Length: 330
Image (cartoon, rainbow, N blue to C red; front, side, top):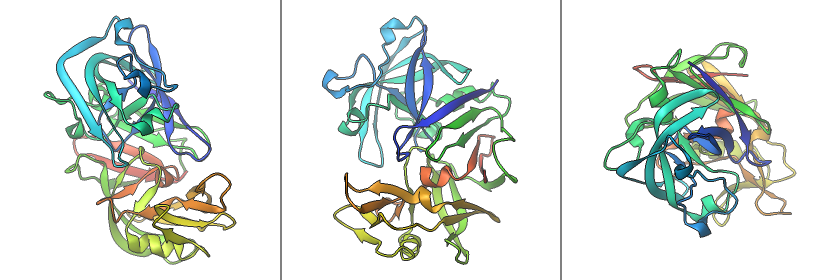
């Protein structure tokens, strides 16, 4: 089998992407944030504290003839941005782009943190990291991809995120018309539960490529590109007037600037992030100070190849017995 679904930016900055997901019988369609940095499929629901729902579409398991409470199971998650959610668990039928999994764990939120409530466009998350990170207790549950992968034509999914435009998540096949050149594959460590790999270096604008190993994760659920302080300083030094602002929380730059590209290495291959992809707009409405899309990871503990990086590529998440990642230009 295969599946193919369009993913759409939630706003004019590409802050996140939503993909429609069918849950239950009859189908309840929710727009979920596909997140290769986490491993829970959780949704706003009829059980979510009413004051914490503000415009989201909810899953109502009592209206699904295939929903079954997973007795005794609870979940609770906290993300790298400080947000969190928790609740109980149902199993139900879940379909993405024509690919159906029966008995998928659907984690129903009883509580969500304010940042989720305040984002009416995201009805939940669909985790695509390794199932070892799934938070369901006392019996850890499998991701949608883990449940589907034996049935797929090939045990892979691909992320093709758009810049200011829709893109595509495919399951089970590699669309050879969706990229240019070849796909360069690179080793993955699953020791932390992430799609963790090592970039071979970087360049700023038309500058020379610096060969240096940068370990990080491919994370569709993170907006920005978080890299070591040395790398980030070298980038913003090429933007007149850019500075790190402790009060704002990262590098800012004059909105009148033209940003240079940023290149990252994948083996001997190179992925070029155009400068425009690094502009996240005014820090507050009407400001002429703009927020940068490349930020230091120094306070995170891990480097993160978020959407800023991934949307410059066609990305293959190869879930073979030994997983690998593939990147192509597009």
